[PDB]
Image (cartoon, rainbow, N blue to C red):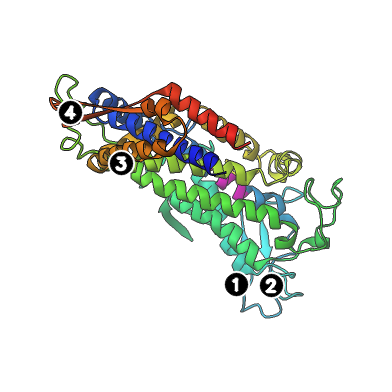
């Protein structure tokens, strides 16, 4: 009915009015502005300077361990690599050291198979093994022997230099590492080699891995369709968090507090508001992305994480952290998802202050226009009430008081009666039923 429609219409105007009002009041308070700026500076440093309690850093870590872990847990069952009949083609014949531990503990592989032609549903080309291996080796060297060598997101120019089996000169930074992680999964997915016996094995699942159930396709991209997909999105989301960290990083400098004793003019003294907004919007995105990484990771069945990744050949052969680089992968996937979820939960207080800082910053950045909007909303509500039955009881839901003495230039002080608002809010949900 038209009356129920009118109430939901008025209620949303009241909500919009109430919120814009609290923000306009907040925009005129240097204490409230100093608190929000101090909150952003603290949570900025907590996102880009910390490792353990940073959902940004832990988001990266899970994407890397999950990319290295997939490769470590199933590379052994990939149809023996090589160039095919013509040894001058497809990367030829090559040998790779420090590869993922196989079912016997072997860490050296030769891609010398000629009996089959490389490609999807067949063997993995030597060139694609070299590609995936290079990416894997960079990830492993970046984590180091301790598994903690990756610098905090604010630090992007730390050099990574080592010799493979060529000499690699790159950066130990999240942008480079996430690209390495993408190379592993993208190359695995497109090359889509065959899995020995079409993945058939001795697990309760019917395949070679617990939690991995064969749906009639024996190739790598068939068997691991869900896991490849979850990991690709994990990389995509954590990469978004890494881009947004540039914004946070550009705003990490400590500012001087506004004088609480002096009058603050919101029309003139808020030139800092634009970067304050961009900082808060970025911090909120980082959080969105870190949580999305959790959600992508949880598409992977629990049995595959606990009874395959946590029981992989790397742990079976005693390759752990703390010379040799065994810091990354399937051995630490399970604890990283715990550390990421825990870091997001511990970011609770900070997350709320970020949203509040964002809204205040947008209001300060657009004060003139936002204040005019408060007036429009007042006029819109007064108009809406006029046609309603018993408009007389409701007329006082909003009120305005003049103050031409205002040193801040806020000549009209707007108000809202919380009780008449509650009544409308509740009368609207009563009419909806």
Would you say residue 63 sits in the magenta stretch? yes
**Disc nearer the start of the sequence (4/1):** 1
- The residue drawn where x is 59% and y is 41% is 294
Q: Which residue is mark 3?
A: 376
Residue 120 in the figure: left or right of residue 357: right
Q: Check disc 1 and report the residue beneath it.
A: 91
Mark 2 near mark 1, Cβ–Cβ under 8 Å? Answer: no
Q: In the rendered structure, which disc, 1 or 3, sits on the residue that comes first in sequence?
A: 1
- Mark closer to the observer (4, 1): 4
Image: magenta residue range: 61-68
User: Marks 2 and 1, Cα distance to the nearest angstrom?
Assistant: 13 Å
Residue highlighted by disc 2? 119
* For residue 86, above or below residue 385: below
Q: Which of the numbered marks, if any, corresponds to residue 26? A: none
Helix, strand or loop at label 3? It is helix
Q: Are marks 1 and 3 in contact (CB under 8 Å)?
A: no
Residue at numbered disc 4:
264
**Residue under the image location 45 percent in, 36 percent down:** 388
Tell me how many marks there are: 4
* Distance Cα–Cα, label 2 vs label 3: 66 Å
């Amino acid at each position: 009915q038209d009356l129920s429609d009118s109430y939901e219409r008025l209620n949303n105007l009241l909500t919009n009015y109430s919120v814009l009002n609290a923000l306009i009041r907040q925009s005129a308070d240097p204490n409230a502005i100093n608190n929000a700026r101090g909150n952003l500076n603290a949570s900025a440093k907590n996102l880009i300077n910390d490792k353990k309690n940073s959902p940004a850093y832990q988001a990266v870590l899970l994407a890397l361990n999950a990319a290295a872990g997939l490769w470590q847990v199933m590379s052994y069952a990939i149809s023996p690599c090589g160039p095919g009949k013509d040894t001058s083609k497809n990367g030829g014949v090559q040998t790779f050291h420090n590869t993922p531990s196989n079912q016997w503990g072997g860490t050296t592989i030769t891609c010398g198979t000629t009996g089959y032609e490389p490609g999807p549903y067949s063997i993995l080309s030597t060139e694609n093994y070299a590609k995936i291996n290079k990416a894997y080796q960079i990830i492993q060297k970046a984590f180091g022997s301790s598994g903690k060598d990756i610098p905090a997101l604010s630090d992007t120019n730390t050099e990574l230099k080592f010799t493979i089996n060529e000499e690699i000169v790159t950066k130990n930074n999240a942008q480079v590492l996430l690209e390495q992680a993408s190379t592993i999964i993208t190359t695995l997915n497109s090359a889509c080699p065959w899995i020995n016996n079409g993945g058939a094995g001795g697990a309760s699942s019917g395949s070679l891995w617990e939690g991995i159930y064969l749906k009639g396709d024996g190739s790598a991209c068939g068997i691991f369709k869900n896991e490849i997909s979850a990991i690709q999105d994990m990389i995509k989301n954590a990469a978004i968090a890494v881009e947004q960290s540039k914004i946070v990083a550009a705003n990490a400098q400590n500012q001087r507090n506004l004088d609480t004793g002096k009058t603050f003019n919101p029309y003139k003294d808020a030139n800092f508001a634009q970067s304050m907004f961009a900082n808060a919007k970025a911090q909120a995105e980082i959080l969105n992305r870190a949580q999305a990484v959790v959600k992508d990771f949880e598409r992977i069945p629990a049995e595959f994480v606990k009874d395959s990744l946590g029981v992989c050949h790397e742990v079976q052969n005693g390759h752990l952290r703390g010379d040799n680089t065994w810091g990354a992968g399937c051995a630490y996937v399970g604890e990283t998802v715990t550390n990421l979820k825990d870091s997001i939960a511990h970011f609770g207080d900070q997350a709320e202050r970020i949203h509040n800082a964002r809204n205040l910053a947008y209001t300060l950045a657009n004060f003139s226009s936002q204040y005019q909007k408060l007036g429009e909303h007042y006029d819109s509500i007064t108009a809406a009430i006029s046609s309603l039955p018993d408009a007389q009881s409701l007329q006082n839901v909003v009120s305005k008081k003049t103050n031409p003495n205002s040193p801040q230039g806020i000549q009209d002080n707007y108000y809202i009666d919380s009780n008449i608002h509650s009544q409308v809010q509740s009368r609207s949900q009563e009419l909806k039923g």
